[PDB]
Image (cartoon, rainbow, N blue to C red; front, side, top):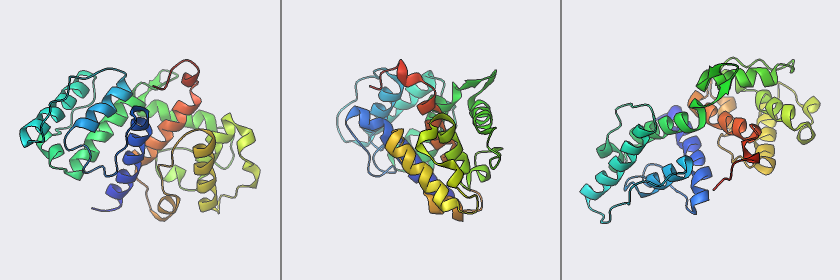
Length: 234
């Protein structure tokens, strides 16, 4: 019920929709649209590329719990970290539990497989960021929160791969709002990465939510991995 939840609500919703758009659907409220399990199963089919069991019909309490359990069984089978998520809480629209469940899904499907110099998962994603921004004198990535507040890290990641898209030299470290908005707009327009973070909130929050930032950064990783050259979106 604070800034942590607010930032995760924004970012996790955006991430989920960046995938569901490939299934011809979208959610409009993350604490309501997964309650019957239907869109949750669809999200899992998109990010895994597999077909889950056929969803049961009927809007009865028992049916919804059934669909959610099908989803929970599927993510367990795919190695998503277990964190005591309960089908009941998901069906009842418990926001804390829902965001917690979505986080484990993001971590498994967008971050865990990342491999960089024998380093993997979150640690691998961080190393990738550090290696790519190494040449930038005004950037020093050391985490997935404070290190990104001035926006230069995001701008540097983009400039490193597509220099023509950002006039990095004109960016000032003491002008974080400008830097963040520049990176977010360029990523949305040229890299097909939806805006998942609110610039003003990043600048105003002593310590921005690392799960939200990690989610956004992982989208940059995938946009620059070259995987799009051999994999069909869906």
